[PDB]
Image (cartoon, rainbow over the protein chains, first blue to last red):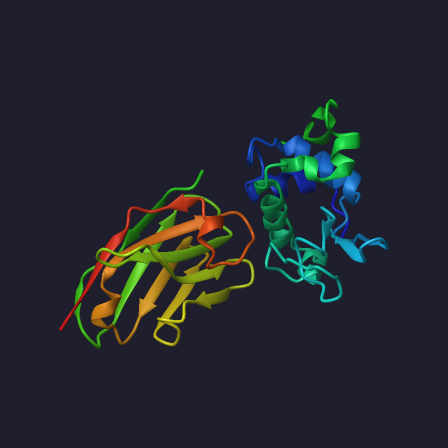
Amino acid sequence: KVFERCELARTLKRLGMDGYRGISLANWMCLAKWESGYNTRATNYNAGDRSTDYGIFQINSRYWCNDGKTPGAVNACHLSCSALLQDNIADAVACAKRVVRDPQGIRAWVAWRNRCQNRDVRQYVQGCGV
Amino acid sequence: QVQLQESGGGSVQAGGSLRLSCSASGYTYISGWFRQAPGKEREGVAAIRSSDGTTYYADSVKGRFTISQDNAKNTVYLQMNSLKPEDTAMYYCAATEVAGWPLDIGIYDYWGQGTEVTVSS
């Protein structure tokens, strides 16, 4: 599914993302926007290490989820990557929280660094009632 | 964040059953029970992932202990059947918002105060 902006902000807020690890809801929204376009079915294949990025937060199959076809798989989230291609985003939200647990935090996502880091992100939560 | 409160601890005779409860004041993804027997290091017992209801048990209690959830009351339960003297311990409820191996102590961020379970004879 493709979430509408405010629909997603309210869902992310209900799932405890706002201020999670010092990360504002607006920053999480910006990440989702540039990673997938708020799309739970987004996928991206990386020919270099043969990994795939999955779902709304584009979680990678090498370190975080198991897709069963990626070399050097760690499965740090202990989740099948297919669980991150679902309309219900609880698993995706939890795995995104696991990514930011690491020292790098939300800087792990290159797109967040190129589009959201040091960017006014007020528009992502404006008028959503969050 | 999330505060956890356990209850149901008590003294039971060997072979008996006991059910512990744990309430959470906010949303949790994974919840589990970690016990500390007298003089020993704390160890994992059982865990549950709330999204799909999958459950994970330590080899020492697998088959005997079962963990469940009541999503309406936001509570988790640890049912223990066929208790042994060796199950005597302070049982702690813990939770996290992160996805990881549910019996990995390192992913847990929220901890209760513990509820004592004593198994005699």
